[PDB]
Length: 234
Length: 234
Image: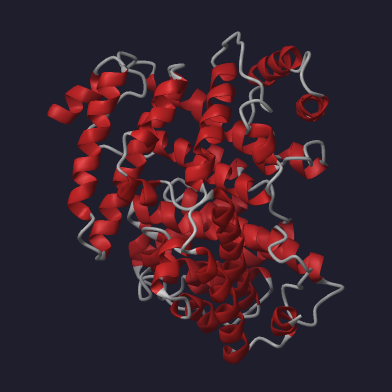
């Protein structure tokens, strides 16, 4: 009741904080117990945190997404963002937000990939693996039933909830493709993994990246050009 | 030198133990340090453990795969198998071994899915997520360069190393499909995600599962029949 009420409110820093605090209280109750049942509860609670992250990405409130990590006490943070996932959460949020907003039609401006550290993170294979792990968690958190009661991704968007989830999960799948086919974008096997993409989403990506690359650092322009080329060849 | 020598020896309980002990020593050196650099080292070391797991699966030594978890001290185990991954490692090893061996042509017998606890694990969405996370780790560990020096997946199999890795990663991708499309196997969108599969591997799966289901518990037979149906419709 109380929890469902929080989750249905308009997305604000206050409502996000109260929701996170509630999930943390449930998580904290499990920490002293190390049997399997507790691990299963904590897995589900983890997905509830990532549902809140993905919902803020989809509602174009990227600052609130980043904030979720801050609002979680460190002992819990160590389990919800294991290992290198803690370090690359900022980049994963940035990339997930960027691609979800392109899919939703947003006409920019997005921040520079080199400036925000995403370009550098891409250069490390272990950071690429951790970013992919987080993008996957964002996606599963809005597909699985993470709460025992249904909760629309975007507050007040009920009849169109399935449509929005479809769009957002397709966006996150493309964000995952960017990471997993870094510097192999136009290989035949890579292009085959774009078969899932609607033609209209593909065109929105092409148009967005064609504007984005203008004036950027040369290495970023080359990267974006490979992605555009792959989209046109698919 | 010493490490490369270990990794090139025939796979035995002794050689596996010595290899794990070496990686643990490197990991233990990182534990007191919590800056980003240490997290990156530990991510790579984690993938080295999973390379050893996948190599034992591919060499039909499933008992040695399970053993890797045992040979890792608990403080390290908490980071390498985070959260629920510790609980479902047994099932992930079982399923990964089963599917890799079908792809390699093995003519059985495999253990009963209900008897070994895999069927029960499938029933829980959070356990399904954790199994998928581990199957993905098995796959990336043999594709990425986890050691600074090249090391063939199967000792003495050098010229055919690329071929074996291709086969094993395709097998693990199909194991992942089984988990991620549990009880939605013959849906149109699910069948589209079988496009990656060679026709001959598809036939080997059909023949193997058709023998496997005989005499099994009815729920296991139904599950296997849905998988077979999906393969035939792809």
